[PDB]
Amino acid sequence: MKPYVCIHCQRQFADPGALQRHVRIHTGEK
Ligand SMILES: [Zn+2]
Image 1 (cartoon, rainbow, N blue to C red):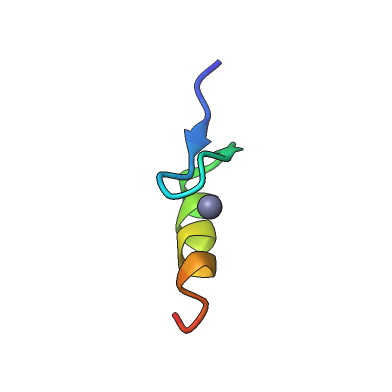
Image 2 (cartoon, rainbow, N blue to C red):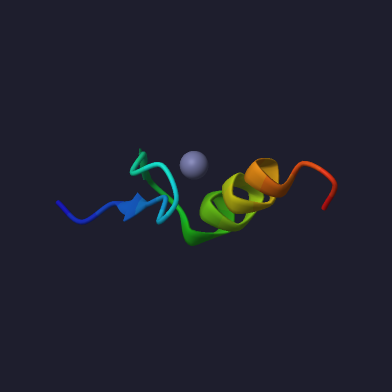
């Protein structure tokens, strides 16, 4: 039902841990 969506690109993920992995992917450098 409820995903964890990327605030920056609006991609729906499962886990909040993946969002943190995801968001830092946008930074790239970190
Ligand atoms: Zn994203």
